[PDB]
Image (spheres, rainbow, N blue to C red):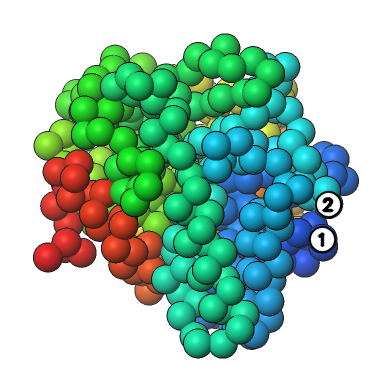
Amino acid sequence: EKQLSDDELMTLVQKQTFRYFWDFAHPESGLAHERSNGGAETATIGGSGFGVMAIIVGIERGFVTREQGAERMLKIVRFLSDKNTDSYHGMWAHWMNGKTGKTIPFSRKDDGADIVESAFMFEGLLAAHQYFTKDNPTENRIRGIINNLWRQAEWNFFTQGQDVMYWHWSPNNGWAMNHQIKGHNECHIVYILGASSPTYPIAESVYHKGWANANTFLNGREYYGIKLPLGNNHGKGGPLFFTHYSYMGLDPRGLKDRYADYEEQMKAHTLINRAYCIDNPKGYKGYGEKCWGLTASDGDKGYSAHSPGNDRGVITPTAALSSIPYAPEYSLEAMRYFYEELGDRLWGEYGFKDAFNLTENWFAPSYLAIDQGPIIVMIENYRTGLIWKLFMSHPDVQKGLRRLGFTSPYLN
């Protein structure tokens, strides 16, 4: 078969992966399954938030019509806002039943609000609020519902009156999960949305003392000749998805606060993760320029948060692919290798399967919402900046970023 151009390849990857969020969505709610080989019943909130962004990409790419996409979006936001769908202080659980809306505990004491998952949902919903701007009954109602959900999200409750934010709260276990959200990981957007709230905002000191002070925050060390501003030391920044989940709507290009240049952060982390793979210090089969990218995913021995400090021989396609706006030539090189060389075993119904290990000759049988979503959306951000422009246009997001001391080309 003749080679696809880069534009053709990108479009095929987006279109095939889009099936996960459109055709494979729960029919009652429009929410995304956590994985293709799990419950029939489980919907994931953070992943569904990526799905919301995937729907906007799909309309713009002509995978569905605007009327179809709006209809689906209305189904989603109606389900999430329904009084019979479980919520806690305006937040949802990590998992819920995709037909009934009842919480499914993620672990024994994690059976209430998950504000990181809910923040990823709001990242998508605020983009959707800024996209569905037509004066017609469906889109008027989409915006109304989203604005009410946004105004009802009680960010400051999750501070317990302290200078930091907590990940969970439960009606049955209160604050027992006791997990402070400390930087620099995937949760940046939680503090930005907290600062942006028109109704339950956090104090600035919550960001500066809670998020911005941790062994895993200021880094500044050099790895393979590259300075990494922030993130885990031993992990050389950590799993690569830390450059994806909060930066689907939040555009890191020209984004700066008193701690970092976020464009530098995302590029440094991506190139270090790649350099680790090229170095291949553990000698795994196939690690290289064509085959790089370590992040959390399924694995031949089970799920793990793979990274240069936890390298188990598993390459995970969402790592390189979703980092496309940060190192496009290198991500396109990995994309083409995954499709053209590994495609007979890695490519299937919903795109690239979750992960593979060439040393153990293993290819994941699964697809995961949280790995598939960023592939669709970050490809689009690279090609047109679509989701970035929508999210960064929201006037509360702009207020929040200013409160926290950010500068950006979107601000002024």
Alpha-carbon neighbours of circle 1 within 10 Å: few (<14), some, or many (≥20)? few
**SS label for mark 1:** loop
Residue depicted at x 76% and y 59%: 29
Quadrant showing the N terminus: bottom right
Distance between mark 2 and mark 1 Cα atoms:
5 Å
Amino acid type, residue under disc 2 in the picture: Lys
Ranked by sequence position, the earlier of labels 2 and 1 is 1
Q: Is residue 42 left or right of residue 272?
A: right
Residue depicted at x 65% and y 29%: 112
Q: Name the residue under label 2.
A: 99
Q: Where is residue 394 in the image (x, y as percent from the top left)?
A: 34, 64
Q: In which quarter of the image is residue 397?
A: bottom left
Q: Is residue 205 left or right of residue 98?
A: left
Residue depicted at x 23% and y 54%: 399
Q: Position of residue 343 (x, y in %)?
A: 68, 57
Amino acid type, residue under disc 1 in the picture: Glu
**SS label for mark 2:** loop
Q: Is residue 49 left or right of residue 256?
A: right
Mark 2 touches mark 1? (CB < 8 Å): yes
Residue depicted at x 79% and y 57%: 26
Quadrant showing the C terminus: bottom left
As displayed, is residue 122 above or below residue 158?
below
Q: Name the residue under label 1.
A: 28
Q: Where is residue 348 in the image (x, y as percent from the top left)?
A: 75, 58
Alpha-carbon neighbours of circle 2 within 10 Å: few (<14), some, or many (≥20)? some
Q: In the image shown, does 54 or 382 lie closer to the viewer?
A: 54
Q: Quadrant of residue 180?
A: top left
Q: Where is residue 119 in the image (x, y as percent from the top left)?
A: 48, 44
Whether residue 217 is visible, yes or no, is no
